[PDB]
Image (cartoon, rainbow, N blue to C red):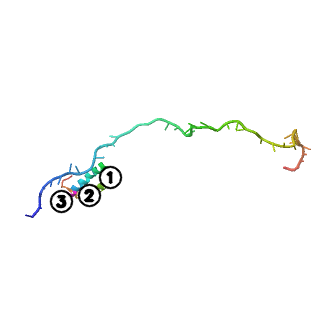
RNA sequence: UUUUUUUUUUUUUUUUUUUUUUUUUUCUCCUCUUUUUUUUUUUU
């Protein structure tokens, strides 16, 4: 479980980039399920990163 | 005996206004027959 988190943060970028395409076309049927996936993917272990973040 | 790297949720907020129910048409139009008109009066 070291490459799973990196695969996750690679997937979330393309799902964050499909919204701009659905908005460009004008088809929010997919642009809504991409927003739901984007909010359904964000966990807290992903953002842990380093020790002295803040 | 299968390594290394590929960032992410638009920036902004400390804008004035001194009025008053309604609202605006329809034309001139043959009234039939015992009458002058009776009348005081009293019991409410």
User: What residue is at 25 percent from the left and 51 percent from the top?
Assistant: A17
Q: A47 left or right of A28?
A: left
Chain ID for label 1? A
Q: Which of marks 2 and 1 is nearer the N terminus?
A: 1
Please state the total of marks drawn on the protein image.
3
- SS for callout 1: helix
- Identity of the residue drawn at 32% across and 52% down: A28
**Of discs 2 and 1, which sits in the foreground?**
1
In the image, the segment drawn in magenta is A4-8
Which residue is tagged 2? A41
- Please report whichever mark, 1 or 3, sits nearer to the chain's N-terminal start: 3
Residue A43 vs B36, above or below: the answer is below
Rounded to the nearest whole Å, what is the CA distance between mark 2 and mark 3?
A: 16 Å
Q: Distance between the residues labelled 1 and 3?
A: 32 Å
The residues tagged by marks 2 and 1 sit, at their Cα atoms, a distance apart of: 19 Å
Pair 1/3: label in front: 1
**Residue A37: image x %, image y %?**
28, 57
Return the residue nearer the eye: A30 or B44: A30
Which element type, helix, strand or loop, lies under badge 3? loop
Q: Where is residue A44 in the image (x, y as percent from the top left)?
A: 24, 58
* Left or right: A14 in relation to B18: left
Is residue A47 visible to us here? no
Residue A26 as seen in the image, left or right of residue B23: left
User: Which residue is disc 3 drawn over?
Assistant: A3
Judge the density around disc 1: few (<14), some (14-19), many (≥20) Cα neighbours within 10 Å. some
Q: Position of residue A10 (x, y in %)?
A: 21, 55
Residue in view at x 26 percent, y 57 percent = A41
Quadrant of res B3: bottom left
Q: Mark 1 points at which residue?
A: A28
Q: Most prominent secondary structure in the magenta stretch?
A: helix
Q: Tell me the chain of label 3.
A: A
């Amino acid at each position: 479980e070291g490459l799973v988190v990196r695969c996750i943060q690679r997937l979330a970028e393309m799902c964050r980039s499909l919204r701009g395409a659905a908005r460009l076309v004008g088809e929010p049927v997919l642009g809504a399920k991409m927003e739901t996936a984007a909010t359904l993917l964000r966990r807290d272990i992903v953002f842990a990163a380093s020790l002295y973040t803040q």
